[PDB]
Length: 32
Length: 54
Image (cartoon, rainbow over all chains, first blue to last red; front, side):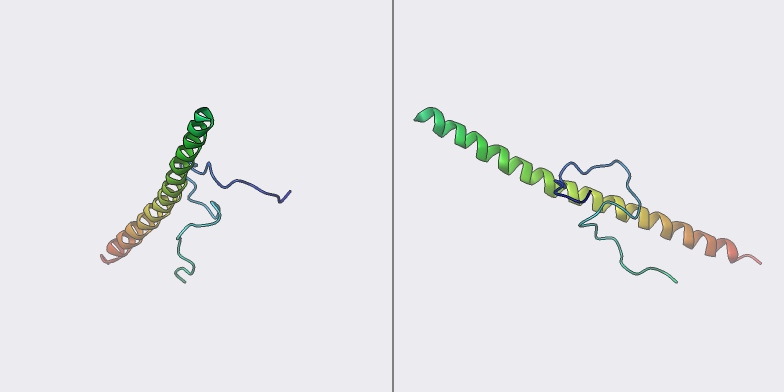
């Protein structure tokens, strides 16, 4: 839908994906 | 009176605890990301090592 979600219970054991929104501190630009 | 006072105190306690909970949540997910990155770096260095033979 797109509506208010509480981004609280947020430990998926391994979300090493283009996912896990909001704060990540991943790197923005990569090798190329 | 005193009943309701104690009620409000329990409320503020649960609040601060869950504050800690959320902060640690974000920290741990960030650690997950970093461990993935270092994994990739390890492999890349290893392929260059293997290409150092011919």
